[PDB]
Amino acid sequence: GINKVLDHLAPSELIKPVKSCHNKPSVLVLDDRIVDAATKDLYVNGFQQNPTPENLQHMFHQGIEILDSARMINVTHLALWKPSSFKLGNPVDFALDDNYDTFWQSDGGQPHQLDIMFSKRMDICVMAIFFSMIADESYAPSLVKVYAGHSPSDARFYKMLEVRNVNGWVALRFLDNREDDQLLKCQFIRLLFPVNHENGKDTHLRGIRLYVPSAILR
Amino acid sequence: YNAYYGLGTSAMKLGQYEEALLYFEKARSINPVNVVLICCCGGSLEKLGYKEKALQYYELACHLQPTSSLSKYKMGQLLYSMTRYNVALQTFEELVKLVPDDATAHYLLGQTYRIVGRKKDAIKELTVAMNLDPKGNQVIIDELQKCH
Amino acid sequence: MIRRAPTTLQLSHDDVTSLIDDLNEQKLKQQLNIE
Amino acid sequence: MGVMYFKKNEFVKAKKYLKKALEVVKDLDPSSRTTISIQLNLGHTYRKLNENEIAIKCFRCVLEKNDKNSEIHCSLGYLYLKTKKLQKAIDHLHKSLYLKPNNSSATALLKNALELNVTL
Image: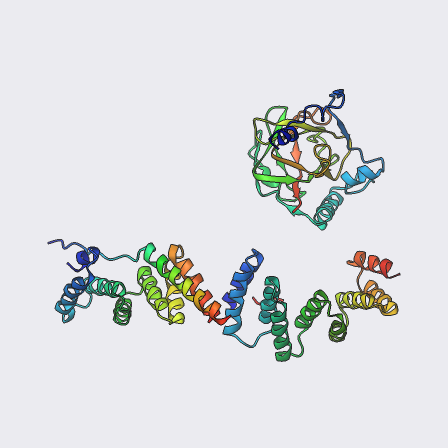
């Protein structure tokens, strides 16, 4: 029994198939001009001239409602946030206020950092980000890399996101890490924005949300 | 009693069902003649698991107020949960007689008719529901497809 | 002369906890008796 | 002497010295923060002597002379919950909560009193 549980803990010959990983970091396509079943799963607002900002606000609200329509638990306000730097005009509150008009802006080094620190082991399943290519082209995020880990010490690369034209909410469920659970299990998530569109300098963040599974008398 | 009702609701929204029920019984004791307090107390009781006592409190409420839409709504929901559809049919029939312009009543009436098996009643009530309101029509469309 | 303010007894937490406990077993006594 | 005999867990003689103190000061000067201490300490001795009626009487008297006192209302809740006068207990306890919202024992006392009242 002792030997067998060690073997289950440490499978020597059982696991390693050929040891032939390609080792390149996998790249995710975010374009919204091609219609596919997989993209529809990750892209919610639907594929479509540039819409007017009031149309962007309208579709911003509809995407929030659609994402919240399904059986879900929102724990966006259940974690600590620490961006790389402020600009004294708008903290991350306007990023997490679920309002298109307001937004958060960083100001500092080019490799902008957004830190998400958790208090308890929460199993995130759907990662939601809203982008606005036409509304914020100057500060649009063009290159996104999402990390993972249990602590600031052991942060590791998870996925790439290249932005070409996404004027809507982006849903990011995770399946590569754990196929059995179809969800991510970490306590430490950080985001990087190393470069912007048309050689930008800073970056806004219109929306951000975290998803987890589980008449009257006045 | 308003403070007691508020304490009961505040306990209810946080999940402390037994504490909420403790508050609601006191709220009922302060004012024995009520309907919404009785409905909330019965809801708390069925949350605990006492379905029969919840039914008795609901019956007392409906006896006290023969014309109470919310009490009959809760009657129907509990009977649907308890698989007592034989009396639930007349409960929703009286309810939809009470409120003719609410699409929610038509939806539940048609759903219960479909569960019983009257296809014509189900399709008629669901068609009325689509005509009245298109906002919640997404569920109504699925109810049509399953019935058809 | 400056008379001192006399000391005042205070209702401790321990005795009130003891009494509240005793009340809990007090109510627990007849609930099984009723059954 | 009454307070120190109380602290020495010897209540019977503390009561006689406090009774003598009350009777000396009974005739003169009901006010001026002296009789208040006398009745409060004497009521505390009765609540520790397990005799409750005269303790309730003295606490009611001192409450008449001073209403803003969270400790007094907490003691009234204690004494009334010791007996089966639940309504007076909860009333005085809510008064104590009103005077001071952040009371440690009072919250548990209110919970127990409400549960007993519901089960009654």
